[PDB]
Image (tube, rainbow, N blue to C red; front, side, top):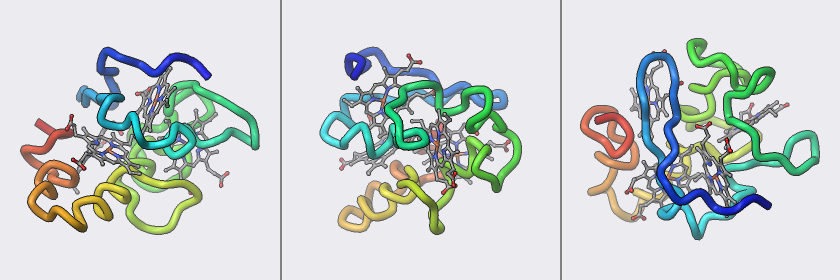
Length: 107
Ligand code: HEC
Ligand code: HEC
Ligand code: HEC
Ligand code: HEC
């Protein structure tokens, strides 16, 4: 593949909306975020019926949370994960690329 999204996409969850810009993640491979599905190309919602549908549960491969605030070991690369490694160089953006309160994610 589809065309790289231009207008920020909303990541509706429980009762909050966290906008996500693709530009910033234009260099980062799509395979990095958009992991293959059963060894097949996909581009459905991160929380599509069957997948990370659960937005409440914390742990679980079906939790939209476990695929965001999961710095531990996983099958793919998490956001907070990369970010952590990213800020690794710029610990001054940790309040943006990891910050819980007043972050590029949580406003
Ligand atoms: C993580 C840093 C990402 C990278 C790298 C790319 N995309 Fe992405 N994409 C990401 C998120 C968090 C979302 C929203 C999921 C949600 O449901 O909240 C998306 C969404 C898309 C879509 C929209 C899917 C739809 O419902 O129609 C498309 C078409 C898409 N992404 C394409 C795309 C391409 C082509 C990328 C590489 C060039 C790419 N994305 C990178 C996160 C990330
Ligand atoms: C993007 C860079 C994020 C950063 C940084 C942090 N979080 Fe987050 N969080 C993010 C999204 C996209 C969502 C919504 C998806 C969903 O699962 O609904 C969330 C949601 C939460 C929640 C709500 C889950 C619930 O309680 O049911 C909480 C409590 C939460 N996030 C906490 C949290 C903390 C403590 C963070 C710092 C370590 C943090 N978030 C960073 C994306 C991002
Ligand atoms: C169903 C078609 C899915 C969609 C859409 C997305 N993911 Fe996913 N993801 C899926 C499964 C079945 C699993 C578990 C792997 C297994 O052991 O079978 C995962 C895993 C992840 C992980 C790692 C967590 C783990 O269990 O190791 C992450 C970080 C992750 N997924 C992120 C992610 C993102 C960002 C998505 C949208 C861009 C996304 N997934 C869509 C199934 C599906
Ligand atoms: C590395 C593999 C990354 C992964 C995985 C995710 N993001 Fe990321 N993010 C990354 C970089 C390099 C940056 C910019 C920091 C810099 O080097 O200057 C970011 C920034 C963001 C932001 C900030 C918004 C903005 O500045 O416009 C947001 C909101 C963000 N990232 C969200 C996000 C989410 C939700 C991810 C998983 C769904 C995610 N990122 C993955 C690198 C990487």
